[PDB]
Image (cartoon, grey):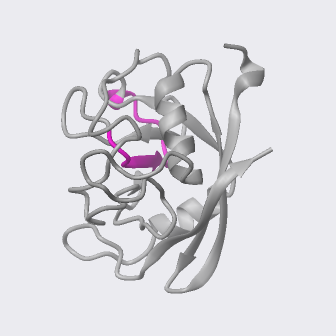
Amino acid sequence: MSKKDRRRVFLDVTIDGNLAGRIVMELYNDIAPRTCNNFLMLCTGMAGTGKISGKPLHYKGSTFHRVIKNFMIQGGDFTKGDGTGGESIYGGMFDDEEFVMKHDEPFVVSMANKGPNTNGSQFFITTTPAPHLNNIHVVFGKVVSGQEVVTKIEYLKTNSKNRPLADVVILNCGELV
């Protein structure tokens, strides 16, 4: 409810086994409670296994399978690891919450989707403002530290499917104080 209700979460990322650093994000629980809760639970793994997939609901070990130079990096697919998988802690996908937050600045954390009301576990971190994505993707967080590890990942050499050649893995993830 209050701005003091905002939680912090972390992602320790490795590129081909070499530690790139830590990405810390502040979740706007007071503006997008369901989306932030889903994300926070996926970082800690404290919600169990997927209802439909029967797989662990948590980012540990998953990758950033898509990076777009000058725009964003995408991850969160813990079931298929290529953009076709992932699952929310609510079972399957969940509805879009009110589009309060906007892509009005770089390093905003937003939900990836496959059309209206199709939120799962996939997300993306932008690197420039993107107002055209407003009212399509639910913004629920902001990177507060480690924005340089985000750009490091973003500029990695990719193939024609926009997939990084190197293995970008979430070594550790969880909650911060």
Q: Where in the figure is residue 74, as x and y percent of width and height?
A: 39, 55
Q: Where in the figure is residue 99, as x and y percent of width and height?
A: 41, 18
Towards the viewer: 136 or 177: 177
Please count the marks in the image: 0
Q: Where in the figure is residue 97, as x and y percent of width and height?
A: 39, 19
Q: Residue at x 25, y 27 (%)?
A: 117
Q: Residue at x 72, y 24 (%)?
A: 5
Q: Where in the figure is residue 120, as x and y percent of width and height?
A: 33, 42
Towards the viewer: 53 or 99: 53
Q: Would residue 107 be visible to someone looking at this image?
A: no
Residue 162: quadrant of the picture? bottom left
| The C terminus sits in image quarter | top right
| The N terminus sits in image quarter | top right
51 relative to 8 in the view: left or right:
left
Q: Is residue 96 above or below residue 98?
A: below
Q: Is residue 130 magenta?
A: yes
Residue 55: quadrant of the picture? bottom left
Q: Is residue 111 above or below residue 12?
A: above
Q: Is residue 116 above or below residue 142?
A: above
Towards the viewer: 40 or 113: 40
Residue range in magenta is 120-133
Q: Is residue 141 magenta?
A: no
Q: Residue at x 20, y 68 (%)?
A: 161
| Residue at the farthest bottom position | 17
Q: Residue at x 21, y 27 (%)?
A: 116
102 relative to 54 in the view: left or right:
right
Q: Is residue 154 above or below residue 17?
A: above
Q: Would residue 21 be visible to someone looking at this image?
A: yes
